[PDB]
Length: 74
DNA sequence: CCGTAGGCACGTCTGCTCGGCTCGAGTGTTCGATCGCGACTGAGGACGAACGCGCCCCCACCCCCTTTTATAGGCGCCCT
Image (cartoon, rainbow, N blue to C red; front, side, top):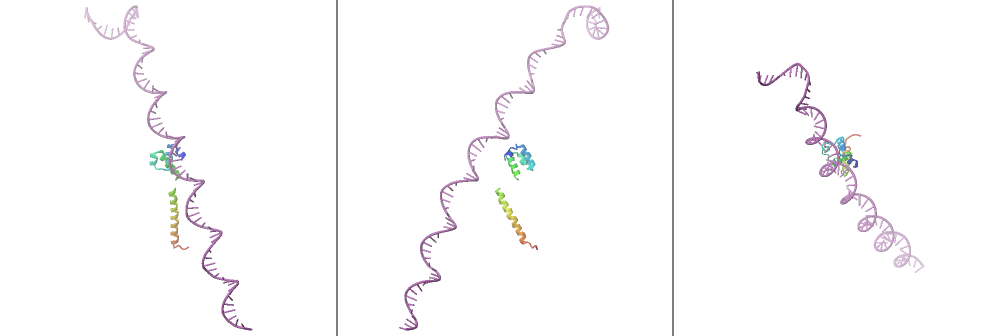
């Protein structure tokens, strides 16, 4: 977070251009918002923890539905 | 005198009581986490001071006013 705020708006603008951030966020260029967006993009937690639980539950549930209903002869 | 019945003793089953063990619930204490506040630092904008630029004025230099005097070609005007 330190060096991202050391980026001195202009180089952070060029970095947001490099990552592929849309031109609206580059255009507004409030520097705190820019550095929060570039920290988020360089990251790209409790809503992900429960979503990964739901994803793991859904995968095996769908897999169990497919195997035990299949009429494939093994 | 003999036979049989009764009484006692021991074994066994269970019914009660006492002791020991273990488990669960609660509360107090201590440690770690998180939040709030203050301080530091970075960035941006505004204000004041100093410098540099532009404009105006002043100063300096050179020529023009005349006279003279020799001497001569050319152009223009004025009265005879």
